[PDB]
Amino acid sequence: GFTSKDTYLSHFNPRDYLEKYYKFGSRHSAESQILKHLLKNLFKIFCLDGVKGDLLIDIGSGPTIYQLLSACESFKEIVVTDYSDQNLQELEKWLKAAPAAFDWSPVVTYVCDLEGNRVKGPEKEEKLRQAVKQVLKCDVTQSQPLGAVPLPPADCVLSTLCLDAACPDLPTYCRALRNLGSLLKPGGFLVIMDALKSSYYMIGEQKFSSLPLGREAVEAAVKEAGYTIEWFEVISQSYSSTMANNEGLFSLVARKLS
Ligand SMILES: Nc1ncnc2c1ncn2[C@@H]1O[C@H](CSCC[C@H](N)C(=O)O)[C@@H](O)[C@H]1O
Ligand SMILES: COc1ccc(C(N)=O)c[n+]1C
């Protein structure tokens, strides 16, 4: 069996998720080490590499913004999407600078440092808030992930830690890659970062399924789905034993063949 989609609407607590994985505490936890590596990869893709354009769609954003910090320097507009309405509400609390919003300042500061300290935290945060115009529902398992909502074909589709959680099997994972491709313009970029060989992840006592994929199956599915791989990186760093049973993480950049 595998976690049903509806479980994300009801049982995925966005504040608990942020507390458990993104607090970015002084302790050199496995979670903070992964967060740092993700940030470095995202900086390399968006600011160092030529990954830019008018529109980036972030798929399965959850309640997080860390994956958009470097992207807001390179894209006029960023659209954040998720299957969960609760997650999108928590994201909107940060976007609207509400009092109950999650404290992203340690991560924001870290991203500013990476980029050369050209700007400081508040200026960086304001650039992200200005870039995010739409907060949409999405279902990666559907041929139209965004439903009846129309969007121009995007220059880039980004998905961090979403596809392993949303796809119950390898054929569904390959179809989800094809479905994301429907949102991309020909030659547009696909950026995926996710756990390798992970069959579950936890949010406190709440268990969530994950599709356990190795690097070869991820690369094969991306090629089967109609992309060409630009680069593929595997990091050996895994989450704490209490959080997930992954054997590292991967990051890839691919281009949609027309
Ligand atoms: N079918 C589906 N379509 C879209 N999003 C889905 C989905 N099934 C699960 N999700 C979402 O996938 C996310 C996994 S958590 C990942 C959040 C964030 N991108 C990060 O990097 O931390 C959750 O927000 C969940 O709601
Ligand atoms: C931190 O969020 C994580 C961590 C690990 C996994 C997994 N697929 O093992 C999934 N998520 C969403």
Image (cartoon, grey):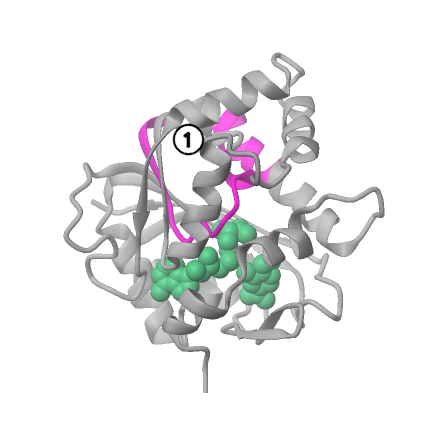
In the rendered image, the quadrant that contains the N terminus is bottom left
Circle 1 Cα neighbour tier, 10 Å, few/some/many (<14 / 14–19 / ≥20): many
Looking at this view, is 110 or 178 the one in front? Answer: 110
Q: Secondary structure at mark 1?
A: loop
Chain part drawn in magenta: 40-68
Residue at 51% x, 30% y is 97
Residue at 66% x, 35% y is 107
Kindly identify the amino acid type of the residue bearing the numbered disc 1. Val
**Above or below: residue 201 compared with residue 118:** below
In the rendered image, the quadrant that contains the C terminus is top left
**Above or below: residue 191 compared with residue 209:** above
- Whole-percent x and y of residue 170? 40, 74
Residue at 75% x, 70% y is 241
- Whole-percent x and y of residue 130? 40, 23
Residue that extends furthest to the top in the rendered view of this protein: 118
Q: Which residue is mark 1?
A: 51
- Whole-percent x and y of residue 147? 19, 55
Q: Ligand 1 lies in which image quarter?
A: bottom left
